Image (tube, coloured by chain):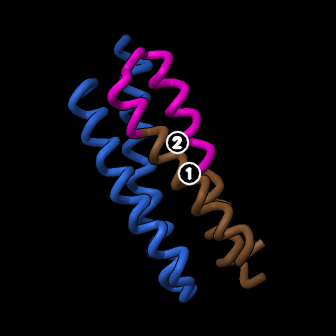
Chain colours: A blue, B brown
Amino acid sequence: MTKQEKTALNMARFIRSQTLTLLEKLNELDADEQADICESLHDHADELYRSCLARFG
Amino acid sequence: MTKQEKTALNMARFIRSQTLTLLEKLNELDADEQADICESLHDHADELYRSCLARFG
């Protein structure tokens, strides 16, 4: 229903944000293997936010 | 250890936590197509944390 569907969409949104913010942090630290994995993680996080926005938006 | 390295690790752990909570909540909402992407996302969140734990913790 609306409140738990909305909060599922809001969790997918802040996870997409957090993968950008952690990629920036990994990049300042010079941690290049981890920064690649986090860039890719941000690709998956995007696809899930789009999927959740399509269903619950 | 740098403080910043620990900020990176805690956030990689958070994303690990939340893609999993969101995965279970998407299964509770019977949202199959979204639960499929979130399981793959959580897997990579888990992978990023293992990598960052080895390097920063």
Residue at position x 44%, y 19% in the image: A4
Span colored in magenta: B15-37
Residue at position x 72%, y 84% in the image: B2
Count the marks: how many?
2
Which residue position is annotated with label 1?
A: B15
- State whether the magenta stretch is mostly helix, strand or loop: helix
Q: Quadrant of residue B35?
A: top left
The picture places residue B10, in percent across and down from the top left corner, at 67, 61
Q: Nearer the viewer, residue B51 or B5?
A: B51
Mark 1, residues whose alpha carbon is within 10 Å: few (<14), some, or many (≥20)?
many
> Which residue is outermost to the top?
A1
**In this rendering, is residue B26 above or below A46?**
above
Mark 2, residues whose alpha carbon is within 10 Å: few (<14), some, or many (≥20)?
many
Marks 1 and 2 on same chain: yes
Q: Does the magenta-highlighted stretch encompass residue B33?
A: yes
Residue at position x 35%, y 15% in the image: A2
The picture places residue A51, in percent across and down from the top left corner, at 27, 36
Q: Secondary structure at mark 1?
A: helix
The residue under label 2 is which amino acid type?
Thr
**In this rendering, is residue A20 above or below A52?**
below
Residue B51's tag is none
Quarter occupied by the N terminus of chain A:
top left
Q: CA distance from mark 1 to mark 2?
A: 6 Å
The picture places residue A34, in percent across and down from the top left corner, at 54, 74
Quarter occupied by the C terminus of chain A:
top left
Q: Chain of mark 2?
A: B
Q: Does the magenta-highlighted stretch encompass residue B55?
A: no
Which residue position is annotated with label 2?
A: B19
